[PDB]
Length: 346
Ligand SMILES: NC(=S)c1cccs1
Ligand SMILES: [Cl-]
Ligand SMILES: [Cl-]
Ligand SMILES: [Cl-]
Ligand SMILES: [Cl-]
Ligand SMILES: [Cl-]
Ligand SMILES: [Cl-]
Ligand SMILES: [Mg+2]
Image (cartoon, helix red, strand yellow):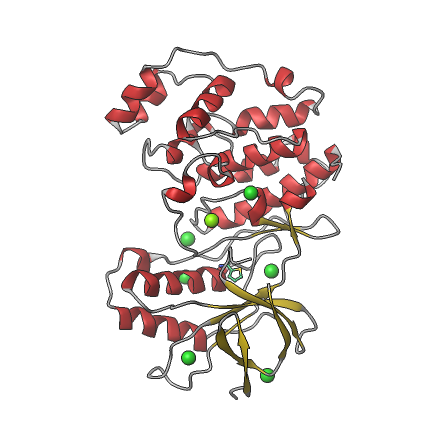
């Protein structure tokens, strides 16, 4: 049966939500227009997001469908999942607003990055790689792993956030900005068609920062950041240069004086030698040669947490819709079907 809804004025608009959600209070806009609430059916504090103008254009309608498909698929301890999705509409004809419910995040990794022991670094990076093995097993690329997208609780337990939101703009990536400091060079500079290996570069940047307390590559712009990267890992050899499909980018790279890879034990002074070894296998310029998430879970650095019988993979994820061309009302009807078919977790 359909639940009873009630109305309240929040975040410049009228929110209409099922009675089970009580004590709504606005909560930053990085993940949308969000309120905290108490869910009386489950006893959890939750985040309720009301989508802004979900079906105003073809691009917005497809983005709404993409976010709902991604959140409905993710079922893993180290990844954000969907607790509920609802609309006050009683038919497709009156369908206009979409609301998403997730666990309420308290702190992200920025706040922690506290005096972190090496045991803390082992456990946090282990959980990121466990979640990433699951994400990559469904042929999803995260593209934006960074400390503000990692939720952490009091017991050091971690979840990965940021799925199905708007692609980052050119201006968001300009200058001295954390949204670019964790990006792999081949996607920062559009060297080539990228793949899931970009996410392992991001994990290496995060792990270095937990070990030192400092941003690894805090570039003041794209070019300054590339110079910091190449000083640490060395300039590319002929094998990688061949793979840079952009003739323009390949030509700029060759204008730079050649530099050897640095000694990571002298960069990360005093760190666990096993941590140094793992960083050298993540922060490889040629993405073909980076360690994978599944391979990294078996690295000796994680020996006290690794359990190959408790590192699950995902059900298959059909993303054929991504190459499909549809009208606004066809994306809207697809979204409506996914709202009404949702089944809550056990
Ligand atoms: N798309 C993401 S990650 C979220 C929606 C509502 C809360 S988080
Ligand atoms: Cl209810
Ligand atoms: Cl969750
Ligand atoms: Cl509606
Ligand atoms: Cl960040
Ligand atoms: Cl798949
Ligand atoms: Cl699917
Ligand atoms: Mg993002």
